[PDB]
Length: 241
Ligand SMILES: C=C(C(=O)O)[C@@H]1OB(O)c2ccccc21
Image 1 (tube, rainbow, N blue to C red):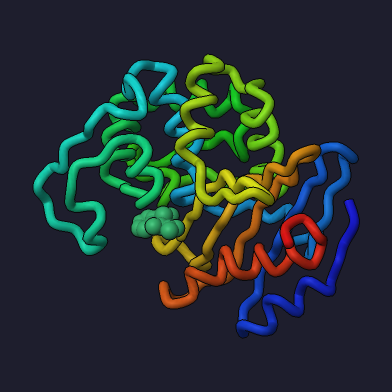
Image 2: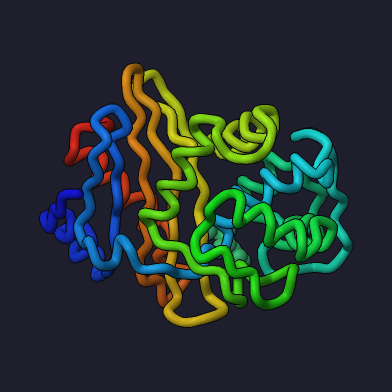
């Protein structure tokens, strides 16, 4: 692991504080601007949608990426949530109430066993079965997110290959002729400190760069900084143009 404090300039530029962690898969080398915060464990918030999706698929709670989960008719503050969703759009718009129903159907015993099998964070699901990743006991650091994502990339988690392929499809965020980004955002607001997350990886022709970032996020107005700061780091390190 190497520390590169120069990336702090990207946070300071936006009056922010946080951490970016990168992992060069070919060379098995990690880089970060803050080795302490890189290993600080936070609520995963919606980044938990990655393991939750895997478990739901593997237990048949979700049949496939086309199955429709009908809106329950309750109007919520995020407009995109007030409609029917499949796994692809529920990941895209981070639709909490769809995933809350998954978790209830999964149930606490199976949720706990799967997170242990995944070696996920502190493996603690204390709290409500349908909100613990938002206001319960589960904590994961940026470097632990990378360990988890690497197993997913390699199809090494303790679920079927199909489940892992479908979730990686549903993580698709950006692609062009230079790179592919598979990732998931998160925003933890229920418990302090409020933080934003972005975790995933960048696929190149001949390498994969895993990343996990979090940043202090006192208001929703800075959420776009999650991707913008990560991309400034990726550009500085010549991973993306
Ligand atoms: C949409 C979100 C994002 O882009 O990060 C966010 O995901 B969750 O952490 C989450 C939970 C409740 C409300 C919003 C969110």
